[PDB]
Image (cartoon, coloured by chain):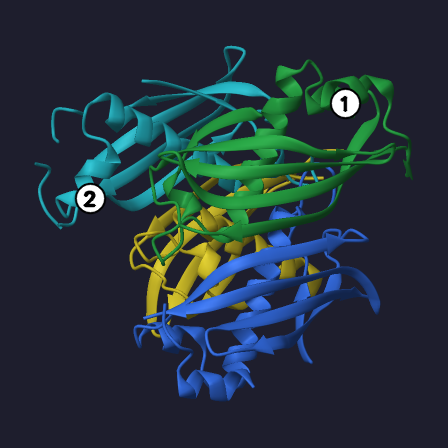
Chain colours: A cyan, B blue, C green, D yellow
Amino acid sequence: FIYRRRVQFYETDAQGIVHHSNYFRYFEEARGEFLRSKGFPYSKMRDMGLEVVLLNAYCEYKKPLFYDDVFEVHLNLTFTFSYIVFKEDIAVAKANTKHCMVKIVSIPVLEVL
Amino acid sequence: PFIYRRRVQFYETDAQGIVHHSNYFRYFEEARGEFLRSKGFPYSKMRDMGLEVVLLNAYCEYKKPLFYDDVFEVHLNLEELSRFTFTFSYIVFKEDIAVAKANTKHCMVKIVSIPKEVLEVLK
Amino acid sequence: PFIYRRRVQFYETDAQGIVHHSNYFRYFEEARGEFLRSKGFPYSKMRDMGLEVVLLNAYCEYKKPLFYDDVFEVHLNLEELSRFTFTFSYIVFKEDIAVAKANTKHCMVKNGKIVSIPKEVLEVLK
Amino acid sequence: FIYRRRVQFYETDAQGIVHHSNYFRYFEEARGEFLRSKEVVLLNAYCEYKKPLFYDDVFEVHLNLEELSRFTFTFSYIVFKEDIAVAKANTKHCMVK
C-alpha cells in the first residue's frame, strides 16, 4: 500500500525537521487508508467492538523531513505492519508496529489485510 | 490570580524556532487543570461524575514568542461565573513580561446548570 | 471563498471522543497553506523570499464537534487587508453544517521587522 | 533518572488512553531533564506498551544510560503507574555539527 502526504508546518520543531514522534502519526494515517481501501476502515471496525490496540513500535531515522516535503509511506504486512518512508524515492526512515484486537480476540478482517 | 509554572518542551516548537500558537491553548488547559485541582475538585473527578466541561470559544493574542527551554507562567483568572457558563482570562509571562493574553468560555453538559459543588470551586 | 478538504485523524481526538480544540488552529493553518499555494505563493516559497507570516491573534467558536474519520471542509475568506495586516475568517463545515467559526490576524516580517505587505503577497491575498 | 509527570487531557485519544506517539514526547522531556541534571540526532526509537495511561494519571519515567560509544549513546526507559510498569522503551542518539 502506498500512502501519500505533505509535511505540515506544525509537524516540525526548532530543529527545522519533522519531530520524530510525528512519524508514528504518519504511520497511523497510512494504516487508516490501507484499511479503508480494503473496505474495512478502522472506523466501521470499532462499531463491532473491535478496537485495534498497539503492542509495540519502532522507527529508524535515516534522513530528515522538512516542512512542505512531499513523501510516501509504504505499508506492508497479532499482526505487525512494516513501513518505509520515501522522499523522492530515497528511504528516509523504516519502521514497524505490532497490533492486536480486543472486542483480546483472534483475528476475525483477517484477509482484508 | 492562579499561577501555573511551566517550561517549553522541544516538541512544542516548530521550524520557525518558536512555540506553535496552537500549543498555547494546551498551556491554558494545563493551567485550568491545576487550578481546579488546587481547589480539591480536579476536572477528572468531574468526569467520573458524568460532568463534562464544553469549550464554547477561545481567544489568544500573541505579543512576544516563547522559545525552547523558556520558563514561563500562565496567570489564570476567573472572569465570569454565570448560571450556565464560566470564563477564564489568561496572561502568559516570561521573565515578568506579558508575551500573550487569552481567554476561554465554557459550559457544562451532563446543556445543564453549573452544579452547586462546581460553582463552589470556581468562585 | 477557498475550500480546504480534510478528514479527521484518530490522534487528533482526545478522551472526550472529539477533536481537541487546539487542533482546529492546525486545520486553519493547513487551509491557509493550500490557499497560498493554490495562488502561486506557497508559504514555503515566501519563507525563501525572506518573508515570515506572523500570527497576531486567533479566535475560534465551537458549535458542534468533529469525530474520528469525519469528513469536513474549511472554507476561508479574506476579511481585511491593510498595508501591514490581513485577516482570514474560517467556517468549518461538516455535511454542509457550520460546526465552527474562527478568524486569525497576521502580519509580515522580514529580517526582524514588520514590513509593508509586498505587492507580491498583496496580489495573491485580495 | 527519575522523571515525574501527569497525563494531560490533550495527550489522550478517542479510545480514552494516551496516544502511543505521545510516549516519545515524554521520553524527550525525561531525557531533557536528565541532561540538565548533569545538535543531537535521533537514530531510532522503540516502545512496548503493556498497560495504558489515562487522563491525568500520575506516572514515573525511569531513565537509564544503557550503551555508550564514541559515536552514539542509548537510553532505556520504563514507565511506572503506581507499582506497575506500563511501558518499556529505548532510543539511540548521535551528534552532528
x 84%, y 34%: residue: C82
Residue B8 vs A63, above or below: the answer is below
Q: Nearer the viewer, residue B62 or D43?
A: B62
Judged left or right of residue D87, residue B24 is right
Judged left or right of residue D43, residue A27 is left
- Give the chain of mark 1: C
Q: Nearer the viewer, residue A77 or D90?
A: A77
Q: Tag 2: residue type?
A: Arg
Q: Position of residue B84 (x, y in %)?
A: 46, 74
Could you say which quadrant of the image residue B75 lies in?
bottom right
Judged left or right of residue A50, residue A64 is right
Q: Position of residue C32 (x, y in %)?
A: 63, 30
Could you say which quadrant of the image residue D54 lies in?
bottom left
Q: Secondary structure beneath disc 2?
A: helix
Which mark is drawn over residue C46?
Answer: 1
Q: Secondary structure beneath disc 1?
A: helix
Residue farthest toward the top in the current orientation of the protein: A89
Q: Position of residue A100 (x, y in %)?
A: 20, 43
Q: Position of residue A86 (x, y in %)?
A: 48, 17
